[PDB]
Image: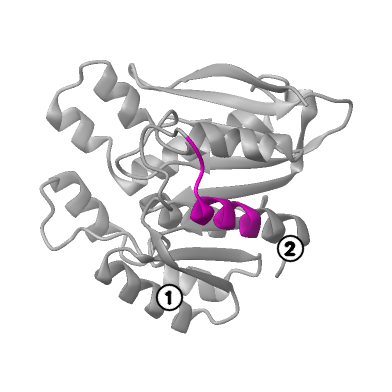
Amino acid sequence: AVVVKKDFRIDLENELFIRGEVTLVEDQIKKPVLVISHGFRGYKDWGFWPYVAAWFAERGFYVVHFDFSRVGALNSGADEASVQKLSTVSRELSDLDAILSNLREHRLPLAEQAETERISLLGHARAGGSNIIFAAEHSYIGSVIAWNGGPPPKAAAGNPNPFINDDVEHNKQRFDTARLLASLTAPVLIIQGGKDREALLEGQQLLKEAAPNQTYISIPDADHSFGGEHPFHHTTPYLEEALEVTHSFITKHYL
């Protein structure tokens, strides 16, 4: 019944780093892994993430959630250009490869309790898209769930961030989650709340039309955070729905 939380830090090139936590209920058996990715404006202690990590730990998962390295750079006093360059989708994918590599090499806390043959991803908002990319590109990711994201990462037209513009420009095919979802044979679930941006709803419709093989769940009255914005004093019906549906999807491998 006791949820334990273990901090870790992965040191990257230069002075970049990822701070994260392993969350689990200890016992004798190896537990399926859920790796969680926060959205563009998020961080591992934001909003619903502490609750969500503990929620999956109470249901028998070895949970990893973490600050993308742009977060650590910002908290370290990096200048605007530095944080901007670290804010690309390519950088998210690199950060994820570091997280997954440390996990799969059994370097994270309490590694003997992780079943790395059963790894799933959960990504929010823009990390919904990056997680689909990562899942499609790595055979060892067994399923992926996107919350209020999933459509291809966009540069708007010309973003305030020129590094994001160059990234999108040079990865048009690589980041095309419509193609990726259509050919990915592993189960993908996208959950979208109906009170989100109109452009995102249109993108989700296009994605569903491109990959009718995957699984799509609408929560019509839910907003971009399922109501779980900061600080998290209590859960909401929308977040509880998203969690139960996601849990059912991971464990059943289908709905």
Mark with earlier residue (1, 2): 1
The residue lying toward the viewer, choosing from 51 and 186, is 51
The answer, for residue 76, to whether it is visible in the render is: yes
Displayed quadrant of residue 222: bottom left
Density class for disc 2 (Cα within 10 Å; few <14, some 14-19, many ≥20) is some
Rendered position, 164 above or below 8: below
**For the residue marked with disc 1, what is the amino acid?**
Leu
Say whether residue 243 is magenta: yes
Where is residue 72? Give x, y as percent. Answer: 34, 22
Residue placed under numbered mark 1 in the picture: 207
**Quadrant housing residue 169:** bottom left
Residues shaded magenta: 234-246
When asked about the image quadrant of residue 198, the answer is bottom left
- Residue 12 belongs to magenta span: no
Q: Position of residue 150 (x, y in %)?
A: 43, 62
Residue shown at 55% from the left, 60% from the top = 136
- Scheme of colours in the image: one colour
41 or 135: nearer the viewer: 41
* Residue that label 2 marks: 253
Q: Quadrant of the C terminus?
A: bottom right
Instruction: Tell me the amino acid under the disc marked 2.
Output: His
